[PDB]
Structures are given as C-alpha cells and as structure tokens.
Amino acid sequence: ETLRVDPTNDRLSALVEIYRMMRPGEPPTREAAESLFENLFFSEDRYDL
Amino acid sequence: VPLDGGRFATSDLNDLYRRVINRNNRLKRLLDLAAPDIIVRNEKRMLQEA
Amino acid sequence: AAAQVLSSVESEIGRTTDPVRMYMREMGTVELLTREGEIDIAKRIEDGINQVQCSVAEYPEAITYLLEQYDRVEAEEARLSDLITGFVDPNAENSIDPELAREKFAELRAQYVVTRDTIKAKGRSHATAQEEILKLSEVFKQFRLVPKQFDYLVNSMRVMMDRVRTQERLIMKLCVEQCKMPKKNFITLFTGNETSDTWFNAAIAMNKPWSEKLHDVSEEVHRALQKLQQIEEETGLTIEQVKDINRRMSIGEAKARRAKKEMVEANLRLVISIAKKYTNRGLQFLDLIQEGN
Amino acid sequence: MGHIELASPTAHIWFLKSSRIGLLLDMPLRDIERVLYFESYVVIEGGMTNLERQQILTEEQYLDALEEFGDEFDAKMGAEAIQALLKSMDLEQECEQL
Image 1 (spheres, rainbow over the protein chains, first blue to last red):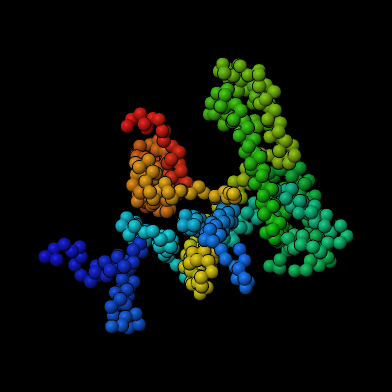
Image 2: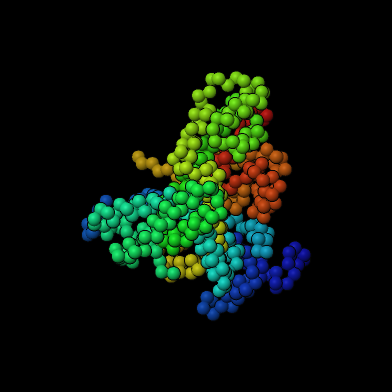
C-alpha cells in the first residue's frame, strides 16, 4: 500500500525525485540525477561509517 | 573606530551599506554599455538581496 | 527545445529563495557554439560595424570635422599628446610620423573639391556625380578612425536625427493636438512640397472650418518651419537625405547589438569557469560573476 | 543622514514578508515573488481583455500574445512593474465596490 501513493515507476523517474528534492530549482538532466545519488550513500570520499 | 595595535573595529551597518552602493554602481555601469538583459536581470536580483 | 525544461519546472520550482539558482537556471539554456559560431558572427559583428562606416561616409561635414580638428592640432606647432592617438589613423590592410600624414593626406583635398562641382553641376543625385561620391567613400574607410573619436562622428548624426524628429514633433504637438488637423493629409505634403510656405495655405485651401480660424498662430506655425529649415539652412542637405542616414545607420547598429547577444550568451559559463578560481571570500559568489560579465 | 538614488525602484521588505502588498493587491505572496525575481511578466493595463489584469505569464506564452496584439497590450516584469501595479488602481473606487 506504500506503492499506491507513489508518483513514479522506475529508476529513470526515481533519480528525478532525488534530484527534485535534494537540488531544488535546477532543471534536471540524466547524469546529474545519476551522479548525486551515486555520491550520497555510495561515495567513498563523502561517506564513512 | 581605531583599536590599539593597528586593528580596527566596525559595526555591521558599514559593510551592508557597501554591498548596496556597488550594486547601485554596477547597475549604473551596465545601462550605458548596452548590456544584455540577462546580465541586467542578474544585477537586479543582487540588489534585491542587498 | 530547451524552454520546456524551464517552464515545466519553473512551474514547479521548490519555492526557490536563492537568486543564483535563478541565474544558473537561465545561463544553461543557451546552447554552446563550437569553432564556427565565433567566426561567422565575428563577420556579422564586423559587417554591421563597417555597414555604419559606409553610412557615416555619406555625411559631407563629418569628414571635414576630422580634418578641421587635424587642422588645429598639427598647426599649433607642437602636439604629441593623447589627441593624436584617437585621430584618423590609417591602418595597413603607432607613432604618427609627420612625414606620412602629409603625403598620404593630399587625396583628401582632391576628393574634397572635385566632389563639390559634379554634385553642383546638373544633379546631386547624378550618376556621373555618384561615382566620385562613390570614389569619396574609398579613401575614407581606409582612414580607420579610433573608436574614441569615431563615436562622436556617429553621435553628430544622432543629435541631428533628434533635431529633425523634435522639429517633426514640434509640428505635431503644436497643431494636431489643438487645431484638430487629421493626419491623413499632412502625410501627403511631407513628400509633397516640404520646402516653403506653399503647403501652409494649401491645407487651408481645403476649407474645413477648423482651417479658417488660423490667424492667431499665423506667426507660430511657419516660424517652426524656418527653424527646421535652419537644419536645411545650416547643412544644405535635404530632409530625406538625413532620413537615408537615419534609416541607413541603424541597420548597421541593429546588426551589431543583435549579434553580440549571440556572442555573449553562448559563452556565459566560461565566465563562471574562472569565477571559482578566485572564489575566496573577498566579495561574493555573484559579485565576481556580474563583474566578469 | 545620507541618501542614495536607486537605479530601479525596489520593494520594501517589511511591507512584503509580514502581508500589506498582496492583501492590498489581491495576489498571493508567493505569486508576487515570481514577478519580482524576473521570471514572469504581469499585466500593467490590459486595454484588451484577452488577458485579465494581474496575470503570471511565462516567457513561452509571452511571444504568443505579443504577435496577436503588438503594442496594444501592457506587460512588464520586475519590482518596478510591481510599482506600476501599485500605481494603476484607485483607492476610493476600489473601496466603493467592497
């Protein structure tokens, strides 16, 4: 039932949402939507547990 | 006012006046130089911040 | 097709309070030109620049003003100040050597007085006279004026377009507002007579009883004719011959500014490229950018 | 005291963010800012009613109506255009209706 209220259906719109909140204002393209979520919880130099 | 060892001291209204005069100066320098409006727009929003 | 990634997203912008992400929103929309857009428009920038230099070549006083100023400084018996930089300066297509501004200066006298008799003789729009005014335009565009003194010689017409147009406006604000002359007939006389007071009673000759009650301003309407014809009386050059410089210079000027909007906005993010290698906290992120523009 | 002329007239913040200028003009505070921030034109004086006054017009549709009406319409964008919006209306006439 969480999948009921969702706007999107796949990765190509999932990185849209992670762009359309973490970076407001900016007209989103592909790699800037790929390279953000790449670097938030999988970057070596900007993450350490 | 001057402090002791060459160091000075200022209120917060000196520098905040400086960011308005220069933006009221750079906008003055754009109009005569027949600037593109996309420069003239982005000058105007910096004054709106200032 | 990049306007929709603005307008479908500027419809949904995240209540954006930062003005950089407004400026950076716009400067990424212009597409970048590679290796030829900076060349064919570099023509178009320069083409409209020297389009004006043919249309300022027509005004017969502007060449002689440059000479009459050159007549002053070299005849003051000592002049190597900052004036001699901005002057005539023919470029090879500089210390002004006083031997070469004399042997390359004889032609501006033989192109001066010959270009007077043939336009005087049997026609000023004359075709045989045209090819010495076509020959006068040869020896002046190689006299490439420095833009410090050249802008004055462009400005010498800009104050005369206005002085014509205000003396066009001083007929429209003094008669049409009050005496109620319908303008569909005054546009017949501007190319109709345009010399003297023969049009003045000609519009009265069309009876139209607003035209009878015109003895209070009898010294007030063709008075303004004699001062607009003072422009004729001071120049000796006809009114549409001004309006073939006013309509012939703008096209060279509306090519220049129109083209520089293409030469600037395709390269706006090269300005932001160096703008973050001096990003240390002197002024601002934006105060360098709007300086860099 | 000293005084500076401003190049363009800019809005006062205590009569914007508090609201005293949207409530005074029947417009949202968020729907003012897009006209201030040089994003969207607003109707100054519509002699032609194809666009009702006080309208947030994108740059895309800005070309569409311009070719239809030429110079017979009025549409500006910026914080001097909001001076023009404040300039147009009448106090006592718009008080008569309410």
